[PDB]
Amino acid sequence: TRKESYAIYVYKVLKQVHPDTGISSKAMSIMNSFVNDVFERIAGEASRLAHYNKRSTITSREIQTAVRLLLPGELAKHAVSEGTKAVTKYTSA
Amino acid sequence: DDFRDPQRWKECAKQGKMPCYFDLIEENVYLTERKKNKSHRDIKRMQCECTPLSKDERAQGEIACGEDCLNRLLMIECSSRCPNGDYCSNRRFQRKQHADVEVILTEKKGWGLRAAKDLPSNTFVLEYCGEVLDHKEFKARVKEYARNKNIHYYFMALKNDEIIDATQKGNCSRFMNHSCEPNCETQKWTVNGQLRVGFFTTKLVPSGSELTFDYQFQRYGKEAQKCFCGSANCRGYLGGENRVS
Amino acid sequence: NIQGITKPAIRRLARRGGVKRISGLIYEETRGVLKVFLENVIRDAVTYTEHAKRKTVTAMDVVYALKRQGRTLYGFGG
Amino acid sequence: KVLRDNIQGITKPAIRRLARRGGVKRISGLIYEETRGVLKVFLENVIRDAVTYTEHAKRKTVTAMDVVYALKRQGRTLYGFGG
Amino acid sequence: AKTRSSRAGLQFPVGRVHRLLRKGNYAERVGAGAPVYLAAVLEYLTAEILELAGNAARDNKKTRIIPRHLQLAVRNDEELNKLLGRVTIAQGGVLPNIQSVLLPK
Amino acid sequence: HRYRPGTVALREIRRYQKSTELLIRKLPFQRLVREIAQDFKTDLRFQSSAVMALQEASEAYLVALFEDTNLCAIHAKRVTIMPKDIQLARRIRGERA
Amino acid sequence: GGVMKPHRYRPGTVALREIRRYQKSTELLIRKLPFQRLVREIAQDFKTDLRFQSSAVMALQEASEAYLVALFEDTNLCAIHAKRVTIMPKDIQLARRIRGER
Ligand SMILES: [Zn+2]
Ligand SMILES: [Zn+2]
Ligand SMILES: [Zn+2]
């Protein structure tokens, strides 16, 4: 049956960054686990923020502040820049 | 004195001024070798964590992979993939960085080597190389040769079931005597996976001093022997009636 | 400012912690650890405040900040 | 078939090897039994949680996902087996 | 372009992210910018980690990134290590480290 | 007369361990908090309750840290906590690198 | 005439060699089948008649080995702080106390 994964997108990114480098099945699974873990943490933090502010929706602001609470300094900064850039590009297009 | 030439001169067996009766050996050759060793399966490369420069020699420079190198502290020499490359000071068995030696008569007991010049402590002198024997072959060759009425038995057990023979072919490190005051010692080094033995010093041997290490007492037959050094506690005879090996 | 955490106060804290003999360099090391701890907690609390669009840091924000850090606090409307 | 004294299956050489991967050089004799106890405690906790999840699931077989959930519960998240 | 990821110029599936957010009971409603933002964050983290993982695999003369590489990468980078400070990587191993007092003199 | 060194400390341990009142005077602590907070954002206000919560958490954390430090120093056959003890404690905790 | 052996290593050297050896690889150190038997016993006492996916056992073993390696690291740290070089049980207890384990 269908067992969804981030395998393909991880491959795309990898080749974007290391075109000439493979990934093992075990490594691929680990990467998938990392992706899911970060997703869950950010989503939970955002939901918590939504609840704390008596708000019934999650917007990119909640995600952004969640990242700011979760990731470290430089990592958080670059992640925030990327997220805002992607949001702006999506809005424009 | 040594005068190693390929033409065999007039010399019966004394190995003095004409050591050209036997054939020399450069590396210990194996007989029953097989791909059942930890050579390239697990120990592929024990690279050292050095960060040399190599851009400063003869001025404020240091010898790479010194006593602070891990490999040297481990009784292991760096491989060809050392970060210095050819400036590594560990590959001494490959480059054959021996020391000055000479074989002459020094006592009626037998031929011996005396230091020619200064030789600081912890310095490679020579290497032990010879024919490595098998299990069933050792017990047969010893008994066949024991009846050959000979005094020198160049037998050295590298491991529990590997004895090296330097009788038929022996390098310069075969004339060394024994005494109760060892100024040298042997060390079991691992180069390229294979185990190798060497000969290092322990003190500031002056110029013109003997170079012998402490043998390990052991007997095989009923007969016994004794030494002739007489340093301070020259036991000579074996340590009791021993039979182990 | 930071030094306002007086050495004897650090001694009192340690005593409540069960310490009997205290070293000189302790005091400053404790000051540093306290500064770091406060930095993290207040950082998170501000972040919470900012997302709330408030110029006044609330207790609740402190509470969520501590809870994030796995240092849950009781007695301020948990 | 009954299972008994399987804790001693964790032989001394194995514990020594682990301690090597931990950066330990010289191992006191009593360390082995204490390590056995610690491992037994940790395994008991993790297996309690995993079995609990399996029970709720109404399954007679423990699945890797159960183990991963249990570990994440213990603040010891593991990558490499899903989730 | 049709794909929302193409609209945002992203490699990850924005649609899948949106579904996930909605099928996770994180809030009553989900905004349209959050899936994009979160997908961008996930992409950025994956790229950052993969860079070091590939570099490590290179250092070990290997064409494929294996778990050892992922470990090495994460544990050597201070920030990544902090993000995954309470995480275990199957087959990860550890960074080679020996305490000073254990070295011979 | 004179109390022998090391006795009044025990009395104080008994004394402080039986009470719960905060041990850092409020105003310097509050000024420290405001100074620290300022570096993240300007013109910020604090509910006194928030400051009290901050102080509660900080003092409780410090007491726990010192408990661990005393444990370490005892293990090191010592009776005087020393910086290295706190460093070891925090390291094992996972707080410091 | 006898056969003599070269020399003997000083203590602790092979300890270091092993340390680097196992710090270079990643393969699991505890043997598999005893571990499986121990796990089966422990589960049995929590509930009878349970079966296991092999992958579940493997994940359990990975987490166990990781936990133990970290524990030994902290133990070694404690041993060093106690001006010693041999880790001793009390070191483990101190590590587990400070960790907040019981
Ligand atoms: Zn080196
Ligand atoms: Zn070298
Ligand atoms: Zn003698």
Image (cartoon, coloured by chain):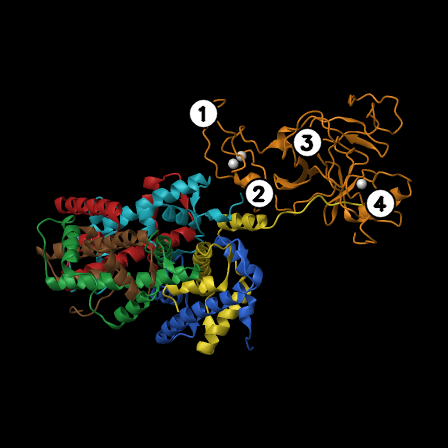
Chain colours: A red, B orange, C brown, D blue, E cyan, F green, G yellow
Residue type for callout 2: Leu
First along the sequence among labels 2 and 3: 2
Disc 2: host chain: B
Q: Residues within 10 Å of mark 4 (few under 14, many from 20)?
A: some
Q: Residue furthest front?
A: F1
Residue named by callout 2: B74
Q: Residues within 10 Å of mark 1 (few under 14, many from 20)?
A: few
SS class of the residue under badge 1? Answer: loop
Q: CA distance from mark 4 to mark 3?
A: 36 Å
Q: CA distance from mark 2 to mark 3?
A: 25 Å
SS class of the residue under badge 2? Answer: loop
Image quadrant where one finds the N terminus of chain F: bottom left
Please name whichever residue, F91 or C22, is drawn nearer the observer in this view of the structure: C22
Q: Are marks 1 and 3 on the same chain?
A: yes
User: Where residue B205 is drawn, which disc sits there?
Assistant: 3
User: Where residue B55 is drawn, which disc sits there?
Assistant: 1
Please name whichever residue, G92 or C66, is drawn nearer the observer in this view of the structure: G92
Q: Are marks 1 and 2 on the same chain?
A: yes
Disc 3: host chain: B
Rendering coords of residue D32 (x, y %): 53, 64
Residue type for callout 4: Val
Q: Are marks 4 and 3 in contact (CB under 8 Å)?
A: no
Q: Are marks 1 and 3 in contact (CB under 8 Å)?
A: no
User: Where residue B142 is drawn, which disc sits there?
Assistant: 4
Q: Residues within 10 Å of mark 3 (few under 14, many from 20)?
A: some
Residue type for callout 1: Lys
Q: CA distance from mark 4 to mark 1?
A: 55 Å
SS class of the residue under badge 4? Answer: helix
Above or below: residue B45 compared with residue D69: above
Disc 4: host chain: B
First along the sequence among labels 2 and 4: 2
